[PDB]
Image 1 (cartoon, protein in one colour):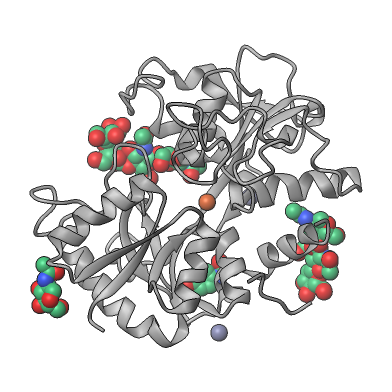
Image 2 (cartoon, helix red, strand yellow):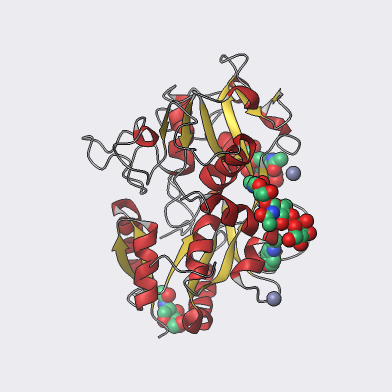
Amino acid sequence: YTRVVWCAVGPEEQKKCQQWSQQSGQNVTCATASTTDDCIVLVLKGEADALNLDGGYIYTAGKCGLVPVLAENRKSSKHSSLDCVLRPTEGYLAVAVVKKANEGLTWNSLKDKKSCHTAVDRTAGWNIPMGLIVNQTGSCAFDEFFSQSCAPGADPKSRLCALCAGDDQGLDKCVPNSKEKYYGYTGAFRCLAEDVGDVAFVKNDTVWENTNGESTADWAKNLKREDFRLLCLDGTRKPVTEAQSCHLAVAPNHAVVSRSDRAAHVEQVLLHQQALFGKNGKNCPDKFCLFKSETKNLLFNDNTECLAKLGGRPTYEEYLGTEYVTAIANLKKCSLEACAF
Ligand SMILES: *[C@@H]1O[C@H](CO)[C@@H](O[C@@H]2O[C@H](CO)[C@@H](O[C@H]3O[C@H](CO)[C@@H](O[C@@H]4O[C@H](CO)[C@@H](O)[C@H](O)[C@@H]4O)[C@H](O)[C@@H]3O)[C@H](O)[C@H]2NC(C)=O)[C@H](O)[C@H]1NC(C)=O
Ligand SMILES: *[C@@H]1O[C@H](CO)[C@@H](O[C@@H]2O[C@H](CO)[C@@H](O[C@@H]3O[C@H](CO)[C@@H](O)[C@H](O)[C@@H]3O)[C@H](O)[C@H]2NC(C)=O)[C@H](O)[C@H]1NC(C)=O
Ligand SMILES: *[C@@H]1O[C@H](CO)[C@@H](O)[C@H](O)[C@H]1NC(C)=O
Ligand SMILES: CC(=O)Nc1ccc(O)cc1
Ligand SMILES: [Fe+3]
Ligand SMILES: [Zn+2]
Ligand SMILES: [Zn+2]
């Protein structure tokens, strides 16, 4: 009851959950699956209680009757006086990033280039940019737009998985979990930085956290913000400082989801868990920090200040917004009330 089973996606999230489990006195416990979808099925079955999902997955989960419980809240400084847990969520910016040196690459010349995506079905990495691209070409053949990609979760023998590298020994190529080298926000940005792809579809924060010494990871130590450009929809290129005027969309924050009938209890445990291991928590940075994992974004994004309560006890459609929800429905016509599982 006052015991929550968290669902970890892959081995590194499993290991981070184990630590949290150990530290919480097993007030929190762990289940592991190989993909986010499998984790969603565990929650549906009642074998896991919760996990923190990107908005594209919140849409999947929502059709299956899962609900948003609490949202990631970022360190942005309006609503000055208001406590993090009560502060409204601001959303993040979906951007398309390229190298400066790749001159004359703009939004209007992306066809046949090489792309890096966080994973199939994700907001900044997939739903937004592909939604736009299908919209613009009036075609559903989005698997033939780019010449090669790393899009975790696509068919390992498609050109959408050609740029993916798998793990330390080349296994698990293109799995939508952190064993894939180029998975997630930092994986997709690394794919661009290493010059495997021509463009990466990530969020604004990813560029900042992995350049100018902010990272220290070996592939990122020498990366410089000036060496990157954002692609705007008007066909221009701007410095990464112009994200407010050069983005593809504003995305709803990642949120914790649970089965409706478990929402209340998952909420109370987690609010208590962040008091202990959150940003200014009793036991962070002393014993354990929930929101840290050295730019790996394990379980939660590394930039999370706190998990915030959601205004208007919203449904999943209200949490995602009509704008975004219609964008997804239209894109999914290419592959009605439903639930995939
Ligand atoms: C696009 O994304 C980036 C990354 O999230 C946004 O840039 C961030 O803006 C924040 C304000 O909204 C900055 O907040 C504070 O960060 C720290 C807090 O201690 C302050 O000093 C920092 O010290 C740490 C050392 O650990 C460094 O990481 C920082 O470089 C900095 O020196 C800082 O003065 C500030 O009060 C945050 O620094 C900043 N992130 C970075 C890495 O520069 C950006 O706003 C966003 N833009 C849009 C359009 O949304
Ligand atoms: C790709 O193109 C599709 C088809 O045009 C886009 O879908 C459309 O998106 C707009 C923008 O939100 C919707 O407009 C809304 O119309 C409803 C009326 O049903 C109204 O209540 C709102 O005030 C708003 O004007 C529109 O409904 C929707 N069209 C439909 C029904 O399919 C889609 O947004 C495009 N994809 C991307 C990523 O932009
Ligand atoms: C877990 O058990 C109870 C229930 O909330 C609580 O009082 C206790 O502080 C928790 N312990 C930890 C370490 O989370
Ligand atoms: C469209 C949109 O983001 N709506 C929304 C976001 C957060 C929330 O707590 C309630 C509603
Ligand atoms: Fe996301
Ligand atoms: Zn905008
Ligand atoms: Zn409502």
